[PDB]
Image 1 (cartoon, protein in one colour):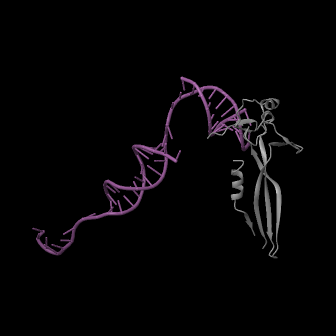
Image 2: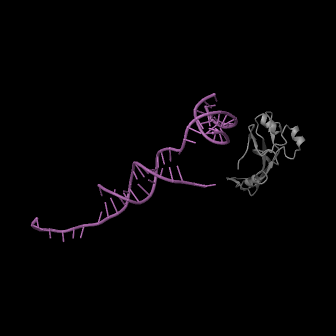
Image 3: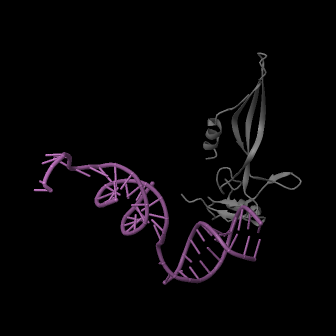
Length: 135
DNA sequence: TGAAAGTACTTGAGCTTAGACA
RNA sequence: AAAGACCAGGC
DNA sequence: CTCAAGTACTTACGCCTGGTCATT
C-alpha cells in the first residue's frame, strides 16, 4: 500500500483543470518519512510506538507530494511552478512494517525502546489504542 | 456475494345482437 | 458524565 | 363494476460482561 498503491492513486488522479487564465495542477511523486511527532512548538521529532501508546498519540507518518502549478495567461508563455515536499496529510504506520521505526531493529534495540521483541507488530496505533485491520 | 413470506392494494378486462308476440 | 452506535466475549 | 394478477409494509432468541468512539 505504501510503496505502490499511494503513488498509483496520486498519479492516476485527473489533473486539476481550472479557468481567461488557466490553472493546471499535477502531482509528481509521494514521499514518506519516518513517523514523527509535531509538538506544540512545532518541532518535529521521531515518535516511538511506546510514546504513541502512552500519550494517546497517533503513530503516523507525514505524506509529501510534488505539485507543479501551470498558469496559462494567453501570452503564449505558460509559467509552471513546482512545489517540493508539499504536506498533504499523515498516514498511520503499521507497526514493524518497512516504514515503521521498529523495522530492522534487533532484540536489544527493541528492549532499549521498551518494545517486546516477541511482539509481531502488524497493527496501527490510533489515539494510543492498538487497532488491527481484519481481512 | 446470496432472505422469505404474508398481507393490503390496483387495474384491466370485457363476456351478442337485433322486434313481435311476452 | 448522558444516550447512541460499533465491536469482542460468557451461558 | 368487478373479478385474478402485480407492487409495497414488516419481522427474524433470552439475557449478561466489557471497551471505544463521536456529539453533547
